[PDB]
Image (cartoon, coloured by chain):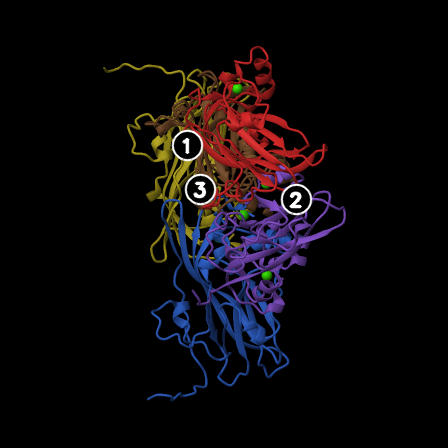
Chain colours: A blue, B yellow, C brown, D purple, E red
Amino acid sequence: QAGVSMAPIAQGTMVKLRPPMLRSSMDVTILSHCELSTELAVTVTIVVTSELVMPFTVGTWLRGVAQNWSKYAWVAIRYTYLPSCPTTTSGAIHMGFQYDMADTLPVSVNQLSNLKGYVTGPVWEGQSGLCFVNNTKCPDTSRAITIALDTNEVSEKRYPFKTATDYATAVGVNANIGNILVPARLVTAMEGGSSKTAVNTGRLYASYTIRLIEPIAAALNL
Amino acid sequence: QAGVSMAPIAQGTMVKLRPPMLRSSMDVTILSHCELSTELAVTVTIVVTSELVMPFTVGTWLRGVAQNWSKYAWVAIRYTYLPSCPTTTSGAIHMGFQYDMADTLPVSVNQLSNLKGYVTGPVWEGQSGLCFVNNTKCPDTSRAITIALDTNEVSEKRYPFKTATDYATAVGVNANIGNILVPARLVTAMEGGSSKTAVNTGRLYASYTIRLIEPIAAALNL
Amino acid sequence: SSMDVTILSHCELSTELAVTVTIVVTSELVMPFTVGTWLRGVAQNWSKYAWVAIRYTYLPSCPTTTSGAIHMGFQYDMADTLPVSVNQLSNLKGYVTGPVWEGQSGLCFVNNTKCPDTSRAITIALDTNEVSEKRYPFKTATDYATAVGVNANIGNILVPARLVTAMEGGSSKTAVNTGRLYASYTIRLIEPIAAALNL
Amino acid sequence: SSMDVTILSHCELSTELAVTVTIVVTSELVMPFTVGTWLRGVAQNWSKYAWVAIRYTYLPSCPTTTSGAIHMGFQYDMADTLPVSVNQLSNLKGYVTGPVWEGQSGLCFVNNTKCPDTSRAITIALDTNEVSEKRYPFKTATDYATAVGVNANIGNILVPARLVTAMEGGSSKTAVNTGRLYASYTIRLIEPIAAALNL
Amino acid sequence: SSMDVTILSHCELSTELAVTVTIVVTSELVMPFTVGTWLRGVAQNWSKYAWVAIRYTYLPSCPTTTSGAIHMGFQYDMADTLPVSVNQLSNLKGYVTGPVWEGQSGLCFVNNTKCPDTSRAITIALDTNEVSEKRYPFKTATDYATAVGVNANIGNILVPARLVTAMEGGSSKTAVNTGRLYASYTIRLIEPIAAALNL
Ligand SMILES: [Ca+2]
Ligand SMILES: [Ca+2]
Ligand SMILES: [Ca+2]
Ligand SMILES: [Ca+2]
Ligand SMILES: [Ca+2]
């Protein structure tokens, strides 16, 4: 049994998220969770969207808690994708990382393909990743559509917690004031398409482990 | 050596707060901390102030974190006081608990004295309590000015997290809609005085242990 | 010290204070320019630097009847907002309070003894691990200021942390002097420059 | 080491110099873009990097009869002022100088020869240990430029250091070509990006 | 070592020289104040010190075609006379000399490079062992000056030694800039004082 596939018509995956895990050592607090991040859809043409890997931006929950603390450090951050359409849908996905907040985004798949977590897959694929979201014991991720921060090669040792707006304002002065506020931005591409009008494909989840560190009341944190 | 006191001129106490402690079991999260709650000052005359023992109201930090979760349960809540003036300052302090949000506050010390944590002391006293704030190993609290919830005799098994404003609005409809939103309110009295104009005395700290329970993003919690 | 690096330790009054009827909240950057005057005049002839250790301590100087308190704590992202209240301040990294007349058990830190009793030293020391930058440039108050004025986020690379001191307490609407705050540091002086040329 | 990490070592021409009657002070940013046009074209393909080593050497091209001297020192606060006098410059970090005709004992750093004489060699290597940032991003002059002009303190985020070179000598108030500056580096390249997209 | 004791090492420009037709003899006190303007600004912050090491090196700035020679020797009785002739000067303590164009093999002391050639290098290091006084106080020129003029024997209390430099060479009876003298020291600073108060 080798070199023999069986093309399904649909990949089913049932996500049942696990409760957040929080645990405090003396001054550091460690949080590990996973929330859903974005929903994706394909078009006849390329489409590059992008995301800040900062805690406010990563999760709806995250932001609300992580905000009670002055500066964090990522320990792990994973973007993993999961399909919703049948294996008949046309179009693939691509993601990779970028780091100088002043760099323009790629416009070509060609381009996109040399970034740090370059990963790509037909839009109907992705169910291998499931354990990462569920966080189960992974089977064989050979084929998953995951991307993970290169946590150890970030520029700052720690980063302050920033609110979107504070960020923005800053960035607006000079885009690379930004280069402190965030360690990296994730880049997404949806090409391959069939409809000129968007077809919804999959959705992707974030899974992190962050160090929290110098308590502040939320109201004062920007 | 018995029945012999030595009147100091001032009670010194150095508070050095301990880092918050958070620890998650599966769905419940447990938080234990202590923050400063109020500052007190005396006057020639009685003065009854009062406080809601709900998480938003208890601490500046608390509120910001506790807000990421749907409903909590108190496990412990302590109000402990500490002096700042010399043992020459006139006026004592009193605190006790109240529970039907519709009940009018006491106006007499007499009155005040039959409430659930009735505790009182000259305004210059209080340094016995220190361990509770520092949380050290307590020496002899015989004479401390502390008050603690009667956690096991609260009305609801769990309470939803309420924002001040949401509370208020509710209360405004009918004061005892309130009776769900909060398990009890602390009552403070400052009499004894000397100046007609307020003299600052001590300050009091809150020390809690709360159960957190059915995660919600902050933005949606009211 | 190496032939490249200089290590310097010292003590100094970083600042003097009083208390009033009401609250007053100050803040002082934990930058060698602002920590004391000597550090200033010395550090000044070095381009970069690194805090090996830094600590603020208080020493009472008023009567046992002066009524009041001191509260110190640390902030680390200059975009953040100085606590309004003491309340907010009791939640910062390093919170500490004490009656304005207590604190002389701390004298050993200005001294260098081995405070057996650190139990009642009103002191505060920086979490140098958790600092964001490996090293820091020597900024002058001015330059710093002007810089911030553009977009506070920039202060984040100009400095490790800001100390917040609250002085609530009082009897007079008239400030009454209570104490003094001294600094104890072990700076890591780093790549010479001629004073005059530094900002 | 070669994974996702790329290491490469090279040696090229950073720039050429000439002397006048008076003193002229220049500065070079020490970033991959501005160090040489080669590295520049190679490094653009990666998002951020860190200097494992870099160093400037000067090689004479004159007769023994020219009149001048080169000087150089590193500076690290994109915000401080350039020296304005030999003396000032004299206490920068790699202070090094000599007559515009001396220097040959430097091929070696260029050359990549093991040569037990540094005897004299107008060479200055960076103190690649005491850089502010763990790593630095690839910044393209024009951007740098732009940013630095918002506030001359942002650059501090973007570059580990700046070389100062002063040409003082003077025979003629005309400009005399005296030699060249060569950079010798070992850089560690790291998050590949399409070249075209790197500001 | 860094307690209450501070050690630091630096290297800077002590002074510049030029040659005439005739012989000119100068002298430099070798005290922190007068050694350089950097040390000077750093040392003022401390009450007394002792030289662990100090040394002057000369670096050419001319063409190979200048005409002169520098000479130098240390002297230790603020009361004896300056030499008046090469010969005399010839038997001072670091006697060293060469043509104003030689010397490059000295960057090294400046440079802080290990270089197996002192082959020739117009360098003179102090015999930091045979100083009269255990330590010396920080004296500020104008004071020194003043005192020495009471009796030229008080200075002997205030400074460990004096450098003598003679510029003899002569092409022109006009003054020709030939190079500079650089000091390289390792000083041990000791009883901190407000700068402003140190005479
Ligand atoms: Ca912040
Ligand atoms: Ca609610
Ligand atoms: Ca500077
Ligand atoms: Ca770039
Ligand atoms: Ca003196």
Provide the chain ID for the residue under circle 2. Answer: E
The amino acid type, in three-letter code, at marker 3 is Thr
From the top left corner, tell me how far across and down residue B150 is, in percent.
Answer: 34, 39
Residue carrying label 3: C128
From the top left corner, tell me how far across and down residue C120 is, in percent.
Answer: 38, 27
Judge left or right: residue C168 versus residue B125. right
Q: Which quadrant of the view contains residue D95?
A: top right
Residue carrying label 2: E65
Marked residue nearer the N-terminal end (1 or 2): 1
Residue carrying label 1: E2
Judge left or right: residue A181 versus residue B71. right
| Residue at image coords 64%, 81% | A196
Disc 3/disc 2 C-alpha distance (Å): 57 Å
Q: Which quadrant of the view contains residue B116?
A: top left
Disc 1/disc 3 C-alpha distance (Å): 20 Å
| Residue at image coords 62%, 31% | E167
The amino acid type, in three-letter code, at marker 2 is Thr
**Which class describes the residues within 10 Å of circle 2: few (<14), some (14-19), or many (20+)?**
few
Provide the chain ID for the residue under circle 1. Answer: E
Q: Which dot, 1 or 3, sits closer to the camera?
A: 1
Residue B188 visible at all: no
Disc 1/disc 2 C-alpha distance (Å): 48 Å
Does mark 1 have its CB less than 8 Å from ligand 5?
no
Asked if badges 1 and 3 are on one and the same chain, I answer no
